[PDB]
C-alpha cells in the first residue's frame, strides 16, 4: 500500500476528555484503524509503535513486537480500545513524546530506518511549552513529525508549529485537519503526502 518504506512509525493518539464519547467510538478509533490500513507493516518495511495519551501515555503496541510488524494483529489491539473506559482525562502530549525520546535514547529504533511520529489530536496539549520543547528535541535527531488535526477545537497555528511549518502561511505536507464526519476520507491523502516527504 501507501507508506511502503523502512520506517519506525510512532502513532500518538489523543484519548483525553476533550473528545466526546460519540466521536471516540464512531470516528477516532475507526480513524486509527484506517490510518494503519495505509501502512505496510512488515519485517523490512514499517514498524509500528502506538500509544494513547490522556493523563499519561499508555503504550498499546510495542515497537518491533509482533503486532508492530503485522497489520492484522495491530488492528485487533486498536479495536480493543473500545473495551476500555476511554476517552478521559487531561491531554498529556508531552508524556507521549517523552516516551518516543526515551526509545531513541535507549537505541531501540532501527539504526537505518527513518523515524516518524504521527499525532492524532482534537485539542491543545496541557503544556504548549513542554510538548514543543520535546518535539524540537526529536526533530533535531532527524525525527519527522506529522500532525492530523480533528474537529473545531484544534489550534491550527500550534499544530503547524509542532510540525515545523509556518503557523499560518504556505503548504504543509506534514499537516492536515478534518471535521469528525470526514476523517476517513482525509487520512488517506494525508498519509500519502507524509510518506513522500519522509522518503526525501
Image (cartoon, grey):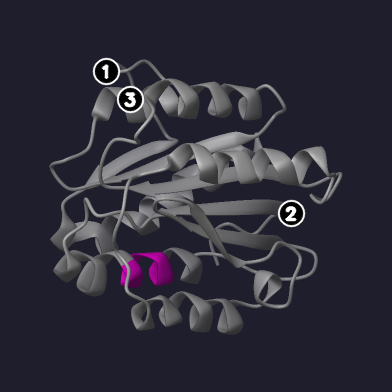
- In this view, the residue in front, 117 or 114, is 117
Quadrant of residue 115 in the image?
top right
- State which tag comes first along the sequence, 1 or 2: 2
Query: Does 93 sit above or below residue 74?
Result: above
Q: Quadrant of the N terminus?
A: bottom right
Between disc 3 and disc 1, the foreground one is 3
Mark 2 element type: loop
Range of magenta residues: 29-34
Between disc 2 and disc 3, the foreground one is 3
- State which tag comes first along the sequence, 2 or 3: 2
| x then y, percent, for residue 116 | 61, 44
Q: Main secondary structure of the magenta part?
A: helix
- In this view, the residue in front, 54 or 181, is 54
The residue that appears at 57% across and 84% down in the rendered structure is 72
The residue that label 3 is drawn on is 158
- In this view, the residue in front, 19 or 195, is 19
| x then y, percent, for residue 113 | 78, 47
Q: 41 left or right of 175? A: right
**CB under 8 Å between callouts 2 and 3?**
no
Q: CA distance from mark 2 to mark 3?
A: 29 Å
Quadrant of residue 143 in the image?
top right
| x then y, percent, for residue 14 | 37, 53
Q: 102 left or right of 122? A: right
Q: Residues within 10 Å of mark 3 (few under 14, many from 20)?
A: some
| x then y, percent, for residue 76 | 50, 84
| 72 part of magenta stretch | no
The residue that label 2 is drawn on is 6
The residue that appears at 26% across and 18% down in the rendered structure is 168
- State which tag comes first along the sequence, 3 or 1: 3
Q: 78 left or right of 85? A: right
Label number found at residue 168? 1
The residue that appears at 32% across and 68% down in the rendered structure is 86
Amino acid at each position: 500500500e501507501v507508506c511502503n518504506d523502512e520506517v519506525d512509525l510512532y502513532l500518538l493518539m489523543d484519548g483525553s476528555g476533550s473528545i466526546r464519547r460519540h466521536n471516540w467510538v464512531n470516528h477516532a478509533v475507526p480513524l486509527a484503524m484506517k490510518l494503519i490500513q495505509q501502512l505496510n507493516l512488515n519485517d523490512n518495511a514499517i514498524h509500528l509503535y502506538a500509544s494513547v495519551f490522556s493523563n499519561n501515555a499508555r503504550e498499546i503496541i510495542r515497537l518491533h513486537s509482533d503486532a508492530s510488524k503485522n497489520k492484522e494483529k495491530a488492528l485487533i489491539i486498536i479495536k480493543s480500545l473500545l473495551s476500555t473506559n476511554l476517552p478521559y482525562g487531561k491531554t498529556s502530549l508531552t508524556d507521549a513524546l517523552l516516551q518516543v525520546r526515551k526509545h531513541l535514547n535507549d537505541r531501540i529504533n532501527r539504526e537505518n530506518a527513518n523515524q516518524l511520529v504521527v499525532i492524532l489530536t482534537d485539542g491543545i496539549p496541557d503544556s504548549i511549552q513542554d510538548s514543543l520543547k520535546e518535539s524540537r528535541k526529536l526533530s533535531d535527531r532527524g525525527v519527522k513529525i506529522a500532525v492530523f488535526g480533528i474537529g473545531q477545537g484544534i489550534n491550527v497555528a500550534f499544530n503547524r508549529f509542532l510540525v515545523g511549518c509556518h503557523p499560518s502561511d504556505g503548504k504543509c505536507n506534514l499537516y492536515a485537519d478534518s471535521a469528525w464526519e470526514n476523517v476517513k476520507n482525509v487520512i488517506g491523502p494525508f498519509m500519502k503526502a507524509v510518506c513522500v516527504e519522509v522518503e526525501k
